[PDB]
Amino acid sequence: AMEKYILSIDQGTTSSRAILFNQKGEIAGVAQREFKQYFPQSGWVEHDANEIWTSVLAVMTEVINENDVRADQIAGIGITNQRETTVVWDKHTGRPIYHAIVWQSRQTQSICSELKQQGYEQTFRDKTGLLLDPYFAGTKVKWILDNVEGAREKAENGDLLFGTIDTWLVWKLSGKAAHITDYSNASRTLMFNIHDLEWDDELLELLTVPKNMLPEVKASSEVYGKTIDYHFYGQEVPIAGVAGDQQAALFGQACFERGDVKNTYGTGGFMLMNTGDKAVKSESGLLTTIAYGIDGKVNYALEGSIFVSGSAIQWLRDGLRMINSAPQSESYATRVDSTEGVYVVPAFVGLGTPYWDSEARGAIFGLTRGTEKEHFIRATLESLCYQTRDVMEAMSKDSGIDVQSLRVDGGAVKNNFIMQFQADIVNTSVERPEIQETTALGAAFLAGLAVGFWESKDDIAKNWKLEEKFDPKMDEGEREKLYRGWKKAVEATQVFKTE
Amino acid sequence: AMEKYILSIDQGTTSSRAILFNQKGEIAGVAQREFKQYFPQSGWVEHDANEIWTSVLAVMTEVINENDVRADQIAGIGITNQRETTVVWDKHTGRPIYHAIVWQSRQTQSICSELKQQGYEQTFRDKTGLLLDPYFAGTKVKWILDNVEGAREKAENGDLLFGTIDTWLVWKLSGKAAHITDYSNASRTLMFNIHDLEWDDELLELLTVPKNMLPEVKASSEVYGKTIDYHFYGQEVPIAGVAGDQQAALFGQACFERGDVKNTYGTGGFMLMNTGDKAVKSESGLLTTIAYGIDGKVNYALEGSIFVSGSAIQWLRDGLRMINSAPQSESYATRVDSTEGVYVVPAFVGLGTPYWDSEARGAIFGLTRGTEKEHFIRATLESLCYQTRDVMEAMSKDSGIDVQSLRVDGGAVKNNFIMQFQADIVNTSVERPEIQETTALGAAFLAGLAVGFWESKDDIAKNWKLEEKFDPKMDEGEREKLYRGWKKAVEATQVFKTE
Ligand code: NA
Ligand code: NA
Ligand code: NA
Ligand code: NA
């Protein structure tokens, strides 16, 4: 028809989403499909990359069939994704050789430990902006090659390809035409040198990964290829935007300049501040990473990473079966006026910023006989806010900027209790936008800019609108007592080590 | 209708029960009524002594009325009770001047802290067999006298009486005719010297308790007085048995000789070993206490005290609202094969034997995204077994004897999962009797003995019947791994302390 749209695919940790955006920046359709989470041992997290692929096909098809947009009205596709999660597959069959190892997974701990013991952690820090934690892709690749029968040989024979999720989806979607990643996704692999913007041969040799398995690193806004016709209703549509999910949210929050910051509350909680054209080092447990590559420039970021944020609330539903839906948690949490000393430390897959303790597991403290369901749920919800304060403190310290207002996005932001508690505990305003799908919006703009659907990234800034600003309303004394109890809870959590 | 019965009152922490026994030792009727638990602040636990008194009247009435046994068929009454719990009342009005302060309550912490600071713990220990923990009566009397307005003045004037629950009930029931306690209950007050067998002047001065408030200390099997007619359907029935509930259970398990031991799983968990006619000092966190006074002799015991045992299960029911009843916990716990590294340390009111840490609160460890309701419940159930093991390691050290089989009673013993896991985690057989209401039976015998209903306590031994012997079937490697994580769980629990 006459109107054209951009299709954005957000392949998350627990679900895949496809959202259509019109010229005005409005959402013209959304579809979401969950896929299985595998936890074969304590702290491991795996996905079936085949199911992830079918979930992406499922949401593309749903969003095109069920709104008023046909495949021929799609001007371009942007792809964004859960970062670090690693897929290794056979290039001829297109079949993965093992589950995708998820970013959260701690299964590559023995590998990180060995590399740390051999004295290489500083080299990885200096070259990648990360550290030797199980979070990153490199060790997941090594794990697959070392532990899966036949993997090593196939790797040696040139039969295998590596990819983060963006890479996997583009290869499948393009009919094997394009094996690529962008700078933001590559920066999370532990194999890409963020300073010289090239795969690093030393790091690859330390990780025992053959260079023949790697995609070509590209900018985040560029026509990488097109959909193979049979995966897009007979049409060949430009695949033109790719960035890691948290970086996409950064771009979708118009945080384009040095000091601009946002926090995303998803499965995990990720605060990123754009540091412009220079990489900034951190002494307080932040990652130095790449924001995006566009217009021939590369922006870097400082990141605070929290492994379990919104997924703490989901655990209350799926795990303990205490609530029917995440939004229902607010009613329980607000039915009491305090947690009465209870803390929940949801270190289900260890602790990220600033602790970086991959052996810690989840714990709960301050329980008494009068602790009710309301208190427990309330404490679970406040853990999203306490973890964010930990990150903010590290971020304000290392950035040298005092954050006077945080833009936020992700599912948990709809929860007024959590947003207000957040503002209170950090004594900083929290701003929730009208369109909270910033990850999708960012990827849509990367693609749309590449195909000339939009002319300027500033449209994002212009279109952004404040839905609600939460202002701190809690005395310094209460705030400081509450936070001291949180830090004590984390301290106690770190003592529980059995492994 | 000719035949006579003994009525046994068990005034527990969460309910009062009245059980009728015939000459054959058979249960001829049971009535139970719950009363309100008050948790006004975290760690505090209070009861309304007026509601305890009406709950007792209620179960006496229900059990006779509903089993067609006439009041004039009761040959005697035995009273047993939650120990330490403290009532202070006006002798003219019979009205308590405050709630009863429960054994569990931590509200007397500061009072214990001051006496410890002043250097007085080892005097309390040497005289009473106890320690300066909020568990015991003495500091509860002081708290009431210091914090209830006008109370100090009324005490000084002779208007007030003190009683543990036994004393309160006997006073009310006899229409103010008898203000007494037995040696077992008195031994738990922090005011009674267990070696000299008398109220201790030094200890009263330190606690600031006037001696005029104290009842007379008697044997556990003696006619103390009779029911006042209007509280017992026009009859004046001998009140002839009084012992602390755990001591009554010891007696009811036929544990009459040196080395005989039982564990009772109730609100709390209590292991007592009879030590014959001599008091044994503990070096490993056991209390030295009085078992009972009968036939002109006084038996002593060693005790391991766990504050939260079966009440952890009740917490799943009324606190987190995860189960409909304690028995339903079994099906969830056995639906999985292990807790997968989850531990539940139910220190809601601190830790008793052997840690004696009154500031510790409840905690949970080892949580992952895959921890489900079933895991959480199972770990909660195992906590009863781990705490018992802690007490058994202590008990074995400060006695010579290593348990060969443990006689058990209380509400949780009906749960086969728990008894089997208990036997497995300690590598010792557990024997569950056919009649599990040993506390009630013990109190019935103390009464019946005193009125000639039974001529010998040997009948308890002869009537006891094994219902099921649980035999350990767990690999030693597994047992040691499991118990090591429990100990680490407790270590981490002890780190969480707030200001
Ligand atoms: Na997700
Ligand atoms: Na359910
Ligand atoms: Na109990
Ligand atoms: Na007899």
Image (cartoon, coloured by chain):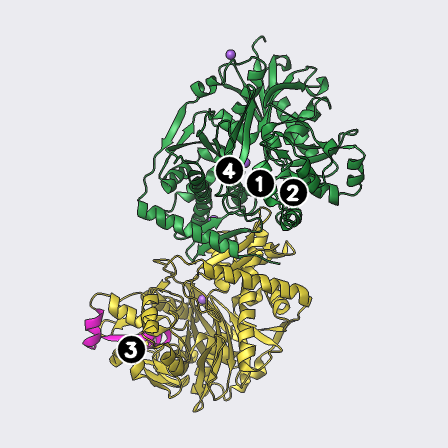
Chain colours: A yellow, B green
Amino acid at circle 1: Arg
Is residue A113 in view from this perspective? yes
Q: In this view, does A147 lie above or below A291?
A: above
x 36%, y 36%: residue: B428
Residue A152 in the magenta stretch? The answer is yes
Q: Nearer the viewer, mark 4 or mark 2?
A: 4
Q: Do the residues labelled 3 and 1 touch (CB within 8 Å)?
A: no
Queried on whether the Cβ of the residue with tag 1 lies below 8 angstroms from ligand 3, the answer reads no
x 37%, y 63%: residue: A45
Structural distance between the alpha carbons of marks 4 and 3: 62 Å
Chain letter belonging to callout 3: A
Q: In this view, does B477 lie above or below A156?
A: above
Magenta segment boundaries in residue numbering? A151-177
**Residue position for label 2:** B38
Apparent side of residue A292 relative to residue B347 in the rendered image (left or right): left
Residue B4 is situated, as x and y percent measured from the top left of the image, at: 57, 12
**Residue position for label 1:** B125
Chain letter belonging to callout 2: B
**Residue position for label 4:** B281
Is residue B437 in view from this perspective? no
Label 1 crowd (10 A; few <14 / some 14-19 / many >=20): some
Quadrant housing the C terminus of chain B: bottom right
SS at mark 3?
Answer: helix
**Residue position for label 3:** A206
- Identify the mark nearer the N-term, 4 or 2: 2
Structural distance between the alpha carbons of marks 4 and 1: 9 Å
Structural distance between the alpha carbons of marks 3 and 1: 63 Å
Residue B382 is situated, as x and y percent measured from the top left of the image, at: 43, 44
